[PDB]
Each structure stands twice: as C-alpha cells, then as structure tokens.
Image (cartoon, rainbow, N blue to C red; front, side):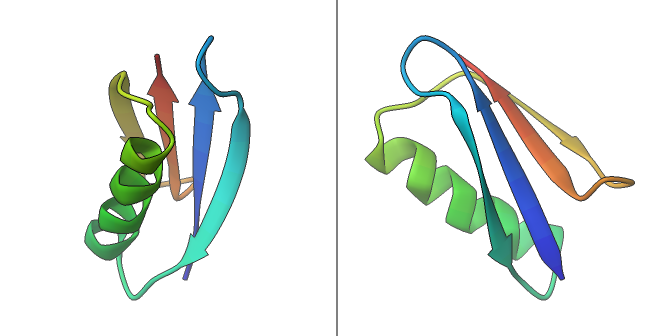
Length: 56
C-alpha cells in the first residue's frame, strides 16, 4: 500500500511516499528518513489518507 509523509517546517518541506504492507512499517521507514534529514516535530497519522504529517 502506498503511504505518504508530509514534512512541514523550517528544517525541510516536502512530501515523500513509500510502499509498505502496513502503516507500522511505513512509519518505520518515514521515521528513519526524517531522522536522516534532521527532522523532529510532532507526528500525526490519518488512516483515511494513509498519510503521516510531521510538523517541525
């Protein structure tokens, strides 16, 4: 399933997607990506849109 990650902030702004079996797996990938790019913020997940939104 395709999951999306919306990054909103002063550190990095953008959107990336990942293919995973579930949201748990997708979240793992996205957390690794956010950390690698120096992003922290508050995370929200919306199941209806399979989207994670991170505010820095």
